Amino acid sequence: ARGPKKHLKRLAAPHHWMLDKLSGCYAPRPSAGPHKLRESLPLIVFLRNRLKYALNGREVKAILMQRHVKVDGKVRTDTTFPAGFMDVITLEATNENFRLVYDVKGRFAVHRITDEEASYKLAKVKKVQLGKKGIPYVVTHDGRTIRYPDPNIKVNDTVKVDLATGTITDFIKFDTGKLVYVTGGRNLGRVGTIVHRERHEGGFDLVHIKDSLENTFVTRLNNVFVIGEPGRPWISLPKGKGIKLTISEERDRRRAQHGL
Amino acid sequence: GISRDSRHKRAATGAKRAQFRKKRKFELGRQAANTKIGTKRIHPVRTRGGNQKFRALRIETGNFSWASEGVARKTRITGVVYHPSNNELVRTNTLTKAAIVQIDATPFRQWYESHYGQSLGKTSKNTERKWAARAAEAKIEHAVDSQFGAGRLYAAISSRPGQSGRCDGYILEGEELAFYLRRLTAKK
Amino acid sequence: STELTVQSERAFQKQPHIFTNPKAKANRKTKRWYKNVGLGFKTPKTAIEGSYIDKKCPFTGLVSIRGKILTGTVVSTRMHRTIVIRRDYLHYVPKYNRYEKRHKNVPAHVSPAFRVQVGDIVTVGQCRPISKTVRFNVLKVASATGKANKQFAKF
RNA sequence: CCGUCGCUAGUACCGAUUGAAUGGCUUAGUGAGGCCUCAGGAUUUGCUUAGAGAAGGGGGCAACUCCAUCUCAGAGCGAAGAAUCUGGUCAAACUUGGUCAUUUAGAGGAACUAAAAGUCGUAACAAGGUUUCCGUAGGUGAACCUGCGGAAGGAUCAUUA
RNA sequence: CGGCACCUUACGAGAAAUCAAAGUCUUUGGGUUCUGGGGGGAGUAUGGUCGCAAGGCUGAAACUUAAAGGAAUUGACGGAA
RNA sequence: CAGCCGCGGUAAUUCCAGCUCCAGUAGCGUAUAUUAAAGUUGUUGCAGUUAAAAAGCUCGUAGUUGAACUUUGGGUCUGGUUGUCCGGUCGGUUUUUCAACCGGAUCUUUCCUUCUGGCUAACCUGUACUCCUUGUGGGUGCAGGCGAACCAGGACUUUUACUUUGAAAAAAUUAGAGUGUUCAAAGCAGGCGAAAGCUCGAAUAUAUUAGCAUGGAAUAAUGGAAUAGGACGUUUGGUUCUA
RNA sequence: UAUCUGGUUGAUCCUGCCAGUAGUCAUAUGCUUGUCUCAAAGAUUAAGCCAUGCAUGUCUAAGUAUAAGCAAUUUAUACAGUGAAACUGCGAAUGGCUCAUUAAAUCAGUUAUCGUUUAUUUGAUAGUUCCUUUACUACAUGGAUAUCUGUGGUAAUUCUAGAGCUAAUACAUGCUUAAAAUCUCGACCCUUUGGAAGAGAUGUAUUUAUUAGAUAAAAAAUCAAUGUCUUCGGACUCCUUGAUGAUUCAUAAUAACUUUUCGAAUCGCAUGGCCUUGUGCUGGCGAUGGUUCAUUCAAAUUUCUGCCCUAUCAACUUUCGAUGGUAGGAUAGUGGCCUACCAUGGUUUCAACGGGUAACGGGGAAUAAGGGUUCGAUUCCGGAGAGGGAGCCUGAGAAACGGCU
Ligand SMILES: [Mg+2]
Ligand SMILES: [Mg+2]
Ligand SMILES: [Mg+2]
Ligand SMILES: [Mg+2]
Ligand SMILES: [Mg+2]
Ligand SMILES: [Mg+2]
Ligand SMILES: [Mg+2]
Ligand SMILES: [Mg+2]
Ligand SMILES: [Mg+2]
Ligand SMILES: [Mg+2]
Ligand SMILES: [Mg+2]
Ligand SMILES: [Mg+2]
Ligand SMILES: [Mg+2]
Ligand SMILES: [Mg+2]
Ligand SMILES: [Mg+2]
Ligand SMILES: [Mg+2]
Ligand SMILES: [Mg+2]
Ligand SMILES: [Mg+2]
Ligand SMILES: [Mg+2]
Ligand SMILES: [Mg+2]
Ligand SMILES: [Mg+2]
Ligand SMILES: [Mg+2]
Ligand SMILES: [Mg+2]
Ligand SMILES: [Mg+2]
Ligand SMILES: [Mg+2]
Ligand SMILES: [Mg+2]
Ligand SMILES: [Mg+2]
Ligand SMILES: [Mg+2]
Ligand SMILES: [Mg+2]
Ligand SMILES: [Mg+2]
Ligand SMILES: [Mg+2]
Ligand SMILES: [Mg+2]
Ligand SMILES: [Mg+2]
Ligand SMILES: [Mg+2]
């Protein structure tokens, strides 16, 4: 209506915040950034509801101002900066380096990553075009645009970005039997190998993907992110490791593991 | 005010679509420019996304282009010779896109005199060699030559001057040109 | 329907930005540009061989096929360069647990590549809005004959 | 137990008033206001070397060992630029008509319903005292009668040769 | 083989008279068209439409009312036997 | 008073008061709607001889429906999945004697879409024949060559409906797991230490209309060779090519 | 958490309704009412009318500050501490409210923009402004306007006329910084194998042209143009090219135009490195701007399928765009969106069109065996509207109403 909408109501807020239904009218609208509103995570939600390093919004703001937070090398001061999938949040006091990675259920898991790994960022490939002055450039689904990529870096590949410099360390070619991580819908957060690629002219390229448990599932190509070669992922994944157990199994795990 | 709504326009069938909402700005369409030829005038208009959009008004001159040679020049227009949408634009003489026009041609001639240097209508020793190397490439399609001789080249203007501001067009050649000529003849 | 005259408006029509070089001397003269539409649809030879222009042709023009690909029988061929497809289908109603026989028509642009008659089954690709209602463009007349050659019975 | 004619209430129906009201469309005529547009030029100024009085008006009588010099008559060349304004265009609204919907006064009419005790009949129910119906015409004070044809829900599943 | 037609049991039915279909239906579904939803107001009002008309087809509501019906049972009664 | 049935006409259990007494209880009545009950709107699931209901009759376009017939049967292995046979075991686990059940490959006069090529994995192999219990236990190994082990491009698909699993159907709601808001209605919390730090969570399922995806080929339609202008191909000519 | 009872009757079994019974984040109301948690609440009639007050403004180490303010004292002989006011910026298009319209419209899911704009966002990034090349704007270009202070009008209004100064990331002008390569021009010699001294032009946007942006396999004969190396029989060899299902795509060149956009005369800290010992040439951390390409926030459209009652609406649309075409115009762009010219289409018993809705759509709500039926003004998502209808400014975004006409 009449131009860009500026608020986000707390029910309309995306579920993988894991916000309270109650406790205020609104939720933080993640501002214009390198990630899509619903597939993002603002710095309020991270430092208040997940980590609980700030008891409230004001506290979070204060922390931001203090400038111990750094989402992907640069500093940030905006409460509602959309830090999305693969973004590396480093709090310099604590030295609690994090990478924003999904849990098997779907929500963003707080992955307490080491200092040596929290340095690069793995990122997908959205486009490969040439800009002005005839220079080829790659675009990432995770924000950045990098000039001059190795000619054999094509669409839907993944790219290890040095992050500090904002360059290209290395890449993985998207292909059959190469470790992949899922970022869309019912399979969001799982991890698998890649078996097929149903081509389909226009209407969404599907991908048959099996996990470590030999459990198959299918997703669209845009909802899949190439994380390594089977056995060696390029990033440390959280406990569970994109398996996603059955409900019964989960229950069993819960009520077997009673260690007071 | 002047809108581009498909809200109005009854329907594919015919039912009178009721006035759902008051029409919006994003649906708007401005008043027509219909540029004549009589002193150079331009007015911009701040469009959507800002973005100025020069409206030609009474536009004299524009770079009309050859095909065969691959060139265009700082060339004046004379008159609206034949517009294939509507003949009201020939009485009023309102220059527009794909209207056929007559081109001052002097500039073109001058350019030719540099380019090939053989003259249309009817020094220095190493440049002679260059000249020899060039020329006898394009013989030109008679009508064009005649136009040149006259001082009035037949073109079709192909820049939309109500949008662009510039009045840049195209020297007519071949089949299309012939057709245009025929049409003109029919008219007169 | 209609066709034949080629260059026959108040204006005169070419494939835009595409050039019939008078200096150069080819046999074709008219440099016929053409599009390969894809999605597993062949460019009909009538389009590449012939003469007609059409902005609204998907093989010899600037209209690009994308989005949905419908099919359907043709009801009306009466208007110029466009067809009225009639896309029959069934609508479910759970209170009874049965179906209706429902209608919807589709006015679609036809490139003179194809000969389209009444009662011909026609595959049609979505594209740019061509007109008021015409948002669709014919790519394959499936019933090429439909017992046209084999009409007479006597041996 | 059925009608007519009475009395008392209420519902709607029709209905002259050249009825009244609201809105929706709408003919013709007008047409506010902006937008573009044709001009129009209050004012504001830059650059021209355009002559000063200036007390080193550029580092010592002098085109100042003349300085964005003292600065207005210049005038030329611009740039921006109001009211005002020529045609469009969008078009509110108004004026007077026309029209559809919904409301709503409305003298009178002609109905129907209710109610416990009105009046003249006894139509139907018993072969209800001319058997009932139905269709249809015609009549009558009201049921109703009576033609014609039909039906039995008939007052007969019956007359043999 | 075909249309204008009795008796018993009904296990099939049906409220019952009765029904060899009015059966194969709460053990609910062979294929179709049409019609009805308490009685009255009313086959009216209105508009349509059809007619030379009489009338036809089409077709309300307001309002009113606890019954209106059906089938049979026993009675009572009948200018029925 | 009484929704309705009805009570009232000098013996009211129904009106108006006391006591008793019932029901519900910090609630209970009344009014209108509406859902249930209503199989009194009926697809499931009603009626039409007489209770309301079969057009007086036939014709008839739409619609709705519509007889049966084309691949059935047998073998040969091979994956599971729970009951069995003991717990072979430290109340749980791994096979066999067995089972039904659901697949898969095939072979049966049988093609599952077919090729132009990439990778031919494999040995149908046999080139030297042997590391070696007396052996067809076992593999360094490469000219002919089994292609399904995958692609990456043609060629052209009879087309549906139906059903399969899948991907998408915002959160709140609904269903629903976990959890001592003191209980619950809720809520997304919490939980455990040295009580110096550590730590579980914030699930899952639905929504079937339409589109997308894939398997299935019964059912129902559709389609094809009867002027065969048909199919193939060692055709043999050609004709138009295109390049 | 599948349930039925009273009522025609003299009694009987049905048709059948009435009546009861139960529920309602369904309203009202009548009595009553101690506590804990929870809490809707001028929708229904009048999208009727409104006194008063409030509901959008806002400055940081970092835009401008000689308030003749505060406060003051141990950076100002151009400035430096705080800062009213005002100009610049940005914001006011969100939010909140309400449900009047609106019935294939909105809306739901589903596609698409190869059909477009997109302040903000984070990623990116511009030696070519010069125009003959022996004496020319740079260590900083210009004049305004507001605060103020002063001269006022008015019955009044968030009213602002005149003078005096006075700024800016105001708003205007405007400097540096080439080599190469490629394309148009050019003093002759020496009879061919022909071959060059040297002069001009070439950023980015803008416009139409025009070229490249290739690509299903191997091997020739020779006819016209006739090139390189000739080891003078002749050889010719290594000859470029992204993405998509798909383009006239990305994009790069040739050609011009252009009332030549842009190309940092910008603010806070810090005050380094070489001496050709000038105050020389040099170099850090940041702010804001500014170009198209990304992205993000979005934006218009747009594909498919789906709405409540009505035949006491069967034809409607098409003079006044209906359907399609061609061309233009317009638009950010598609498009009968509008104009011209032509064709006669387009929809419809698979209910078009019309009428009604005490209809905003959906999520959902109530009821609750299964199937259903009714409700959805209302906490979320969309859409509309700001008394009605119209028009427009500013702006990335409004046809805004706590903007204007
Ligand atoms: Mg696509
Ligand atoms: Mg812009
Ligand atoms: Mg006017
Ligand atoms: Mg008698
Ligand atoms: Mg009698
Ligand atoms: Mg009698
Ligand atoms: Mg009589
Ligand atoms: Mg009735
Ligand atoms: Mg008593
Ligand atoms: Mg009901
Ligand atoms: Mg019934
Ligand atoms: Mg009957
Ligand atoms: Mg009858
Ligand atoms: Mg009859
Ligand atoms: Mg059959
Ligand atoms: Mg629950
Ligand atoms: Mg029920
Ligand atoms: Mg009775
Ligand atoms: Mg009784
Ligand atoms: Mg009831
Ligand atoms: Mg109200
Ligand atoms: Mg809002
Ligand atoms: Mg080309
Ligand atoms: Mg291009
Ligand atoms: Mg057009
Ligand atoms: Mg509703
Ligand atoms: Mg309404
Ligand atoms: Mg609603
Ligand atoms: Mg309302
Ligand atoms: Mg809302
Ligand atoms: Mg009001
Ligand atoms: Mg307004
Ligand atoms: Mg207000
Ligand atoms: Mg507002």
Image (tube, coloured by chain):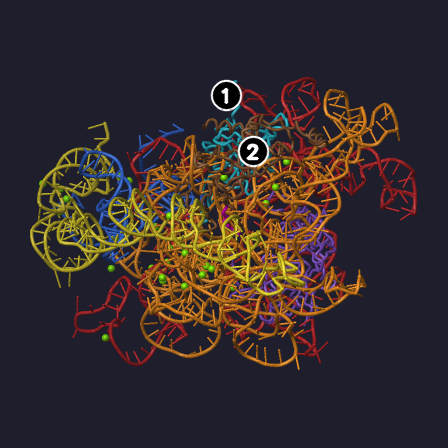
Chain colours: A purple, B brown, C cyan, D yellow, E blue, F red, G orange
Type of amino acid under label 2: Ala
Image x and y of residue E1, in percent: 40, 29
Side (left or right) of G10 relative to G287: left
**Which residues lie in the magenta part?**
B42-50
How far apart are labels 2 and 1 at the CA level? 70 Å
SS type, badge 1: loop
Q: Is residue B16 located in the magenta-colored stretch of the structure?
A: no
Q: Position of residue F26 (x, y in %)?
A: 41, 74
Nearer to me, F15 or F243: F243
Quarter-of-image position of residue B112: top right
Magenta segment main secondary structure: loop
Q: Which residue is mark 2?
A: B105
In this rendering, the answer to whether E64 lies above or below A49 is above
Q: How many marks?
A: 2
Question: Is ligand 23 within 8 Å of the beta carbon of the residue shown at mark 2?
Answer: no
SS at circle 2:
loop
Residue behind mark 1? C153
Q: Is residue C17 above or below residue G122?
A: above
Residue B47 shown in magenta:
yes
Q: Quadrant of ligand 23?
A: top right
Quarter of the rendering containing residue G275: bottom right
Residue F239: percent from the left, percent from the top? 63, 19
- Please state the chain letter of the residue tagged with numbered disc 2 in the rendered image: B
Q: Report in which chain the residue with disc 1 lies.
A: C
**Residue F108 location (% of width, % of height):** 68, 33
